[PDB]
Image (cartoon, rainbow, N blue to C red):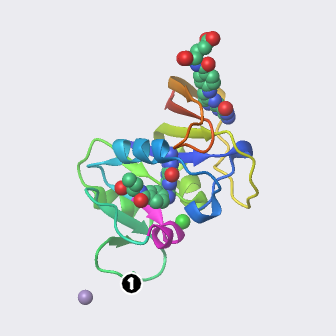
Amino acid sequence: MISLIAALAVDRVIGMENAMPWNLPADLAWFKRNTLDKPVIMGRHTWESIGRPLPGRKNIILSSQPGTDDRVTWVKSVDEAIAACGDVPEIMVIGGGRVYEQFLPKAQKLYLTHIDAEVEGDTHFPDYEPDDWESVFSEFHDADAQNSHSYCFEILERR
Ligand SMILES: Nc1nc(=O)c2c([nH]1)NCC(CNc1ccc(C(=O)N[C@@H](CCC(=O)O)C(=O)O)cc1)=N2
Ligand SMILES: [Cl-]
Ligand SMILES: [Mn+2]
């Protein structure tokens, strides 16, 4: 099964780390926890922002063009990407925007962090029809000394 994971601001805006104005260790801990030991698929731009392979995870980069780093697995198509994951129970799609869009229709679960922040951005997470998804977990957190803004973690499953 394919699952998408992402941190959304108001308006479904998403953006790279440095582009994002919040500092949320709790959300990074959640991302870590839900992706560990699973293969992760990301776009080139995401790969470049991350800087190094995420440890304990098979890193697959979807890109039309040739790879430039032997530490990760380069694939050229969405099908190729799934094939490279092998026989695993859950594949995590970590963005960015275009990658999310390509995998949404194949996805069965979404792990979302809704951050209470207004920020400008080009990029938005794909529109998904709420009636087509069921919320199975939600949990609100206020901001604190460590965490810049308030957030709500949510897990949705395709009905
Ligand atoms: N687009 C979108 N934006 C959001 O802000 C959003 C969303 N989707 N998805 C999930 C979500 C979760 N937000 C929230 C907000 C408040 C509580 C909350 O008050 N929880 C209390 C229960 C209080 C009551 O029923 O009075 C709790 O402690 O569980 C939980 C989740 N927020
Ligand atoms: Cl990307
Ligand atoms: Mn070499």
Q: Position of residue 12 (x, y in %)?
A: 69, 46
Q: Nearer the viewer, residue 101 or 135?
A: 135
Q: How many marks?
A: 1
Nearest the viewer among 83 and 142 is: 142
In this view, 131 is above or below 143: above
Does the magenta portion include 138? no
* Above or below: residue 73 compared with residue 146: below
Q: Which span of residues is magenta-colored?
A: 41-50
Q: Residue at x 31, y 59 (%)?
A: 83
Residue 92 appears at what percent x and percent y? 40, 49
Magenta part, dominant SS? helix
* Tag 1 residue: 68
- Residue at 35% x, 42% y is 33
Does residue 147 appear in the picture of this structure? yes
User: Which residue, as the protein is rendered here, is positioned at the far front?
Assistant: 145
Image quarter in which the N terminus is found: top left
SS at mark 1 in the image? loop
Relative depth, front residue between 19 and 23? 23
Going by the numbered disc 1, the residue's amino acid type is Thr
Residue 41, percent from left and from top? 41, 59
Whether residue 11 sits left or right of residue 114 in the image: it is right
Q: Position of residue 112 (x, y in %)?
A: 54, 39
Residue at image point 37% right, 70% down? 52
Horizontally, residue 114 falls left or right of residue 156, namely right
Residue 106 in sight from this viewpoint: no
Q: Is residue 37 above or below residue 116?
A: below
Foreground of the two, 118 or 84? 118
